[PDB]
Image (cartoon, rainbow, N blue to C red; front, side, top):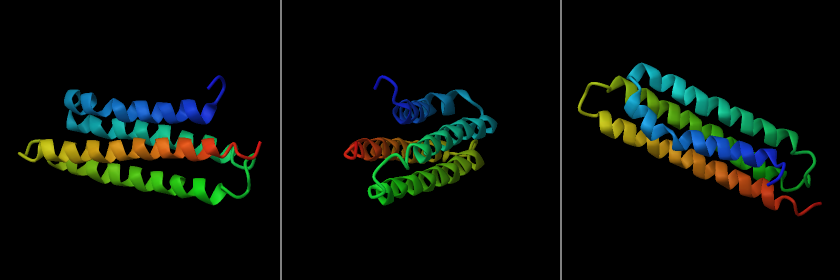
Length: 127
């Protein structure tokens, strides 16, 4: 884009999700919370910028976008649960698997962010 906000926003969340692997390896367990809080905040920002530019779109394809938005919050809620397991097992031999499931949740949150991008995108069918 040249001024698309919802896009730049989606690309931010995708970037924050992309930065997770290195951070879980350089941060102590205590720090995993702040990292996910950022993903958390970047998501809320996005979900918000979409809600604003939502009434400017066909009052039809609205049930479709609201559909992914609810999906995203589901995604984050799961990422948090995983992150909590990732913590409780910081010094057990289940560390790697916990982190692995954390990253898997994060990847699906970006995949869903991208699906959201596309939905609101194609939604330029109105004007």
